[PDB]
Image (cartoon, rainbow, N blue to C red):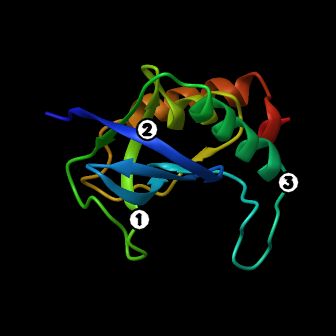
Amino acid sequence: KLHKEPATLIKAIDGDTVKLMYKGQPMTFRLLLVDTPETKHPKKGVEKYGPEASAFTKKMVENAKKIEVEFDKGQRSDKYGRGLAYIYADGKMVNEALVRQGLAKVAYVYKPNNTHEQHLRKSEAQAKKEKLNIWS
């Protein structure tokens, strides 16, 4: 029953986080089910492939005509107040694109927020087989 809703980009913040206008409110969104290397790591700062993951997410959302967010069936925000969602740029899921490119791993999954888990895991297996980026 997952449905997509429109949103407007405000700012990409990191590989795994984008700020969007949603239902007329600015909101920070964390991409569901993926871990990217970070530029804003609480303890490490800027990890390896972090600038790259960050640039990938940025370009993909900044250059899209349409951004949509899709909540999963469980919790829609985390303990930091970030929305938890799948983000689409012109119909293409940003979460999957990162994983397919070897710029994210599939995260530890917490049910029931696991609807696209298999699909993402499939893309991660492919990126690993192609030895892309993080897997190189």
Residue picked out by circle 2: 87
N-terminal label among 3 and 1? 3
Q: Nearer the viewer, residue 96 or 4?
A: 4
Distance of label 3 from label 1 (alpha carbons): 24 Å
Mark 3 touching mark 1, by CB under 8 A? Answer: no
Q: Is residue 39 above or below residue 70?
A: below
In the displayed image of the protein, which residue is found farthest to the front? 24
Which quadrant: the C terminus?
top right
Q: Is residue 91 left or right of residue 4?
A: right
Q: Residue at x 61, y 34 (%)?
A: 62
Q: Residue at x 40, y 59 (%)?
A: 27
- Residue 26 occupies which quadrant of the picture? bottom left
How far across and how far down the image is residue 11, in percent?
58, 50
In the displayed image of the protein, which residue is found farthest to the left? 1
Residue picked out by circle 3: 48
Q: Residue at x 32, y 49 (%)?
A: 22
Q: Residue at x 78, y 52 (%)?
A: 50
Is disc 1 surrounded by few (<14), some (14 to 19) or many (20+) residues within 10 Å? some
Type of residue at label 3?
Answer: Lys
- Determine whether the residue tagged by mark 1 lies in a helix, strand or loop: loop
Q: Nearer the viewer, residue 61 or 72?
A: 61
- Determine whether the residue tagged by mark 3 lies in a helix, strand or loop: loop
- Residue 64 occupies which quadrant of the picture? top right
Mark closer to the observer (2, 3): 2
Type of residue at label 1?
Answer: Arg
Distance of label 2 from label 1 (alpha carbons): 13 Å
Is disc 3 surrounded by few (<14), some (14 to 19) or many (20+) residues within 10 Å? few
Residue picked out by circle 1: 82
